[PDB]
């Protein structure tokens, strides 16, 4: 028992991280088969980052202008292309450590692990949620661009995030591995509105079920509610509306705990209206929304990976 | 910027995890060079776990009674010995993935990453602190024994924890890699008092400095304090006494932020006496004590590992 914010084991991804240098900019790239993926703003100087014409800036570059280093070894770049906001550098060597992998575009509310990297070397790993407003609340310093977020299903790594920038508000923005930004952000240093962020209701309920499984249960009450009534409260507290799809994915947890989803919503309603009165749930004094229902079942059932 | 509970990259440790079977018990072992380390209670049946005589129970076992599996390959056991509460199985093959490593006994308040494993396969990674009472607040299910906690310094893995059991209170207990339990616990299924746990004061202060570095600063006040006065309050709130050694290790953070350690204690004093008034610090509504001062500098400076 016990419940922790648990990241995937990072070994499969560690073997894919390389360092990419262009001019005086160095950041991280992802080496899969014979292609290295990295943020296209690697080709930018500081004077270019206001309103960069990436097409024009990439034209001034040739294969030999991109230095790719995996550990202490050189890769040789034999082709380069831009896909949306990512650069794809073809190298002459397939990565011998390439895992089975897929590129996925995650939906808001879904979670993933982030391997924070500097100079092509792993620094640490943590679990993140894609916020409803398509930012992530990460931990990234200068040099971390090109760090990736991922999920693992047995032996297959699904890459879903590449880190591109920090907004002036201190939150983070990036792309999928096809180079499409999550949200409305662009890779230029301008003012960018993140937009109102809400709480991922289905994830809070998942965590409340996790709490019950683990012995934290003072918050269970003698009330129930309806989808519509609960959604009235959700709107008041800037929670995402609950749908029957969300109820359906909470099914397995309701079966495990014997607590109907709408009864757990009624507990959540009272917690929203009355607070926690200075108590805690799973070691937290606020409502946690970065565990999906799959995350809770995964952790509480001990699923492993190759 | 941003501050997250960050675990070490787990790849070096992933390559050391094996499955160990004895009788009908299967758990995790750590394969370093030609030795596999695992909890000695692998040799126990359920009827033995009340008052096991491990010496007598190990006498009934020979090398061929221990099945060690690394992935899908067999290791052959050519020697077995008991060191305190760990079994050391000599195998005929040195682990080709053995990292540079050391065995360390950590002190209370120090942190480490835990690679939770089942059947010799990694399930996830999270950051833990050794509580002052020598328990850890982990996430462990049946099958997780032999999962290990570790730190990494560049290319060297310092193993500090092997998971052995869950106490009836739901917290976790285990040994260093020489098999000495942390705390007063024993590997038998009996009643075991954890003892009063306190908050790791120096870690809370480290996190408050982390908050300031990251823009969370409403809690800075116009007061100061003295070691003795602050320690009066610490005692009242079940915080560990602050010593000049603790002040000294907070030096680098005070220099970075320009906030004297005793001024930060005065902020902590007011937070202890007045609470947070429904506000948050680094996304938390309670005072966090699982970041050491080194952890904060490590995360805020982007230290990497080979
Ligand atoms: C990419 O590595 C990168 C990183 C930053 C940056 C700075 C501070 C915090 C932070 N969090 N995520 C990213 C962060 C800034 C960069 O440039 C200013 C940057 O590299 C891009 C670059 O150097 N140019 C000129 C495009
Ligand atoms: C070791 O893998 C192990 C694990 C448990 C156990 C059960 C539930 C939660 C939990 N958290 N950490 C460890 C936990 C219980 C075991 O045996 C009852 C156990 O293996 C030891 C064993 O099977 N015997 C009989 C010694």
Image (cartoon, coloured by chain):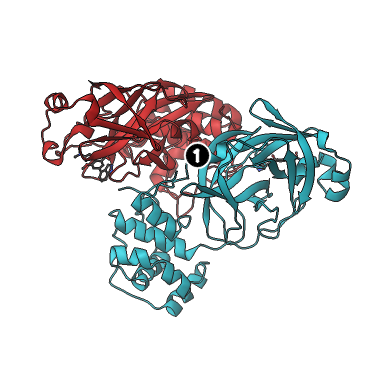
Chain colours: A cyan, B red
Quarter of the rendering occupied by the C terminus of chain B? top right
The answer, for residue A34, to whether it is visible in the render is yes
Give the number of marks.
1
Quarter of the rendering occupied by the N terminus of chain B? top right
Give the quarter of the image for residue B52. Answer: top left
The crowding category of the residue bearing disc 1, from other C-alpha atoms within 10 Å (few below 14, some 14 to 19, many at least 20), is: many
Instruction: Determine the chain carrying the residue at label 1.
Output: B
Residue B202: x and y, percent?
43, 31
Split into quadrants, the picture shows ligand 2 in the one at top left
Query: Circle 1 sits on which residue?
Result: B6
The image shows residue B204, relative to residue A243, as above or below, that is above
The image shows residue B167, relative to residue A255, as above or below, that is above
Tag 1 secondary structure = loop
The answer, for residue A276, to whether it is visible in the render is no
Give the quarter of the image for residue A78. Answer: top right
At a point 33% along the width and 66% down the height, the residue shown is A254
Residue B30: x and y, percent?
36, 29
The image shows residue B278, relative to residue B105, as above or below, that is below
Residue B57: x and y, percent?
14, 28
Q: Which of B37 and A26 is in front in this view?
A: B37
Q: In this view, does B192 lie to the left or right of B115?
A: left
Q: Is residue A69 left or right of residue B175?
A: right
Residue A296: x and y, percent?
39, 56
Q: Nearer the viewer, residue B170 or B68?
A: B68
Q: Which of B281 and A200 is in front in this view?
A: A200
Q: Is mark 1 within 8 Å of ligand 1?
A: no
């Amino acid at each position: 028992s016990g419940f922790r914010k648990m990241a995937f084991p990072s070994g499969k991804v560690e073997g894919c991280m390389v360092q990419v240098t262009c001019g005086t900019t160095t950041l991280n790239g992802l080496w899969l088969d014979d292609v290295v993926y990295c943020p296209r703003h690697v080709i930018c100087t500081s004077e270019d980052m206001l309103n960069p014409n990436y097409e024009d800036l990439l034209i001034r570059k040739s294969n030999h202008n991109f230095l790719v280093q995996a550990g202490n070894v050189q890769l040789r770049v034999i082709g380069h292309s831009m896909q949306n906001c990512v650069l794809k550098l073809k190298v002459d060597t397939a990565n011998p450590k390439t895992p089975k992998y897929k590129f996925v575009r995650i939906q808001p509310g879904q979670t993933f692990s982030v391997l924070a990297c500097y100079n092509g070397s792993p620094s640490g790993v943590y679990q993140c949620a894609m916020r409803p407003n398509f930012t992530i609340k990460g931990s990234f310093l200068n040099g971390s661009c090109g760090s990736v977020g991922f999920n693992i299903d047995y032996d297959c790594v699904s890459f879903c995030y590449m880190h591109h920038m920090e907004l002036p508000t201190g939150v983070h923005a990036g792309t999928d591995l096809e180079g499409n930004f999550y949200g409305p952000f662009v890779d230029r240093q301008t003012a960018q509105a993140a937009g109102t962020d809400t709480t991922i209701t289905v994830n809070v309920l998942a965590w409340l079920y996790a709490a019950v499984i683990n012995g934290d249960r003072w918050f269970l009450n003698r009330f129930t509610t309806t989808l519509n009534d609960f959604n009235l409260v959700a709107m008041k507290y800037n929670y995402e509306p609950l749908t029957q799809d969300h109820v359906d994915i909470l099914g397995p947890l309701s079966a495990q705990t014997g607590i109907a989803v709408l009864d757990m919503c009624a507990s959540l309603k009272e917690l929203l209206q009355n607070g926690m009165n200075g108590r805690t749930i799973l070691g937290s004094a606020l409502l946690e929304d970065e565990f999906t229902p799959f995350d809770v079942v995964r952790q509480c059932s001990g699923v492993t990976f190759q």
